[PDB]
Image 1 (spheres, protein in one colour):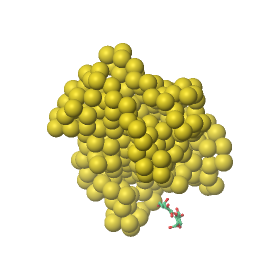
Image 2 (cartoon, rainbow over the protein chains, first blue to last red):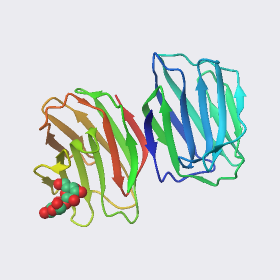
Image 3 (cartoon, rainbow over the protein chains, first blue to last red):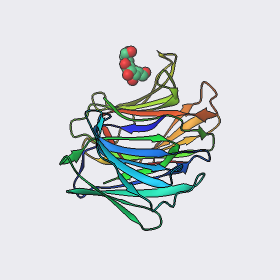
Image 4 (cartoon, rainbow over the protein chains, first blue to last red):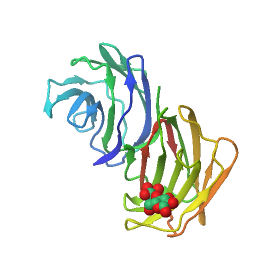
Length: 130
Length: 130
Ligand SMILES: OC[C@H]1O[C@@H](O[C@H]2[C@H](O)[C@@H](O)[C@H](O)O[C@@H]2CO)[C@H](O)[C@@H](O)[C@H]1O
């Protein structure tokens, strides 16, 4: 379910967002979604424990686009983790705890991200945006 | 007017929450609301620029209880402000940047808070809950 939702971010290129939180002992997945509203997302970052893969995708009027899969998966159920997202113009970059970077294109050319939600087995304990 | 909403907080007595953010240049008020759901609030903390007062209250099934008004008002439109809230057994203590504390009684004897929202002219930039 919906853990966290924020509206009216005014997050722009050069922006950095730091999300720390607890992954449920029973999690099968969680997602950090960034866009302009629930049905329009620049970045859906979704670690999936069953397939041991991080899937990224974008959502356009509630239509999912073509996903990207990263098999560098060092997430653990029951743990507290820090995820850093950077809004880098033509792409998003997600830095993981092990220092791996997941890169995802800013396909639809957002210049501002106003909406965030976090769903699934992830309880936010710290959030910072600049 | 809804800016930030979290569910499943699992925040318990002895916990501390830090909410720092930017008060809109054109803000008239903002509110930090903590409780069990949007209709049952242990704490509604509402600084109002049109009255220069902080109104506090609790909400019991969409009924407001007795207001507590704090005339100590050192808030400024357009500024960034850090607010700390401590969940104690008898009360919520809200620590303000200038050292003033607002003590609001824990009228409904909550020992767990699962719901937070922030409304109005306040953009969170740093949130932490423990
Ligand atoms: O008590 C919190 C509650 O206040 C409402 O506004 C009040 C106002 O504080 C009071 O002085 C006047 O007599 O009645 C108003 C309406 O009941 C707000 O509507 C609500 O948002 C809360 O902030």
